[PDB]
Length: 7
Length: 7
Length: 308
Length: 308
Ligand SMILES: [Cl-]
Ligand SMILES: [Cl-]
Image (cartoon, rainbow over all chains, first blue to last red; front, side, top):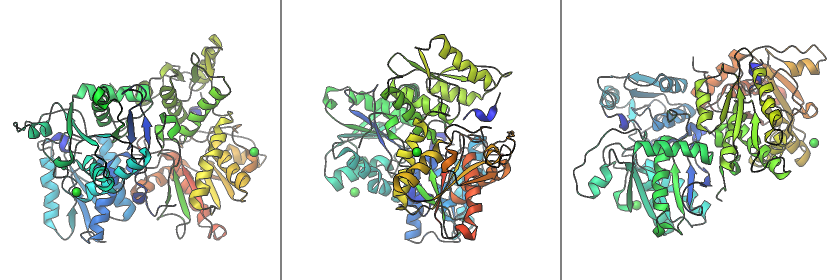
């Protein structure tokens, strides 16, 4: 659920 | 009070 | 090839050929979003500040006024910050928090006006601080300032000439101040000497230019084509270099902007949709079949609400 | 000098010298907002699509997948629309209406995932449609795709070399995929042969690169520097060409972005504030006194919420 993975 | 004057 | 500040970085914006508009690719767009501040107004924004400096109506100690919280407000704000001037912008209290925060993010001394008043609650207000110290405040007036079309004549227009190898036949542009079509038109017809066709675009809802040209009664009205359709003849629109006037409604403009995004991959503002729609109309006339038509896309989506 | 579509219009983005940062103007920024789609990811977005075509893993009839609804999601969306491909983007249902409407404005077939799930509720989802027809869907994977740094090596890096007349000493860039610093670094050190200093930037909060390099335990954490700090070593970050690693916290990043707008007149995103802050730190070391430092500003404000 990695938020800062949505680059 | 011309709205479309705010360009 | 490094710029001394963000103001010097204006222009050299790209020409893209449209695929789902015009005929055999005759409709080419100029992308004015590719500027600092992200609007066509970056150009004038720089040069009206440059000019007032050059002729010495602007100096360290003078602070700038206007009531535009549109693209010219953002243009001036960026340039003021780049170049050490503090800016005050008039603007009714009726405005959006996000422009109120875009500008307060840019260091504008925003001067909330009146939601009983609009752009008179603004225009007249700005003047009053211009009044309360006319050696302090200085107001640039994009609608009548020659440094407005001058920049277009010296950058926007030539870039088109050069990109197209002097092939451009037609130029299509929506009118707010008129500076784009005026400067562009003077560059190409006067400095280069090619007899192209200059098309101003205006809303069908507020079609004051056509009405003037036809010797009819001037009758402005509301529309949604933000950035154009002021409701009068700007002193910056040179009616003389204007060959043609096309009208466009808000829905079509609005739909043409959605199409640009979704079909062309081009992040067009609402005015950009207006200008394309009118270029397409010409583009599909056998009379402009073999003619290279260049369209100004003044602004980028994302600044917008064409997203219903 | 006309582009066949919006994808071909990437790059030649400008270099502006900073006035309230560094020392005697040694800190120069590259403005990546001046692209179609308005992010650094426009470049890779074009070329990953170009590449998959060139090697024939993409064709009329194949539809593209990924779960990035960040700058690479917008990049791919614009390119897909320009070039006739339909795009599906995975994305948890937790996302913002305005990106949900930016992308649905761009013609993305958005696939709302799970707010019990995040980027696993996405990453794993995209795969499943890739699974349910692996001759239909094709997924580009920006974190490991060579066409990612390749574009930087062939455009971003050379443009810097050329603009600076091979004067550039240092290059500073935040790391998401790593493709920028990797491509840029390979261009300048390998294709040109100048031994510059490559500084990766990462959040102090999630400092996985430094932790790796120091042979410590890798410990990712939350931050607000949107676009960087993935929480792992991307296969697109060539750890080999990386000379230095600077960490930056969310507040400073955030404050440096506000300063850029308000002091420099430069419409910086949050990642852009991170990269500057770290460049400034180096810039004020006598060891980098006489050194020209170039910083990547990946994105523009307005896409953002650095406006509290
Ligand atoms: Cl003249
Ligand atoms: Cl290599």
